[PDB]
Amino acid sequence: NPEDWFTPDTCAYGDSNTAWTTCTTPGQTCYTCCSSCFDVVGEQACQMSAQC
Image (cartoon, rainbow, N blue to C red):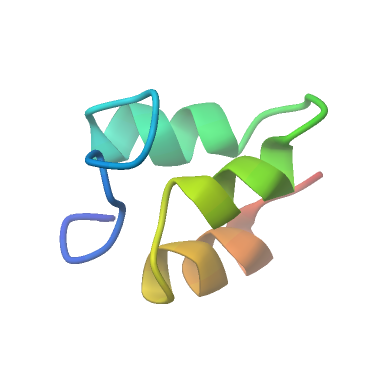
């Protein structure tokens, strides 16, 4: 869970769940959002997770 990661202070989504989830979806900034919805773990974790 992106509880220790994910920064809702610098992302549209204020939730780490919906954020990660909404991040792990088909779009234009699927892997780019992670770079704007995480720090290092959230991004590095969303990086591999992100199936885009």
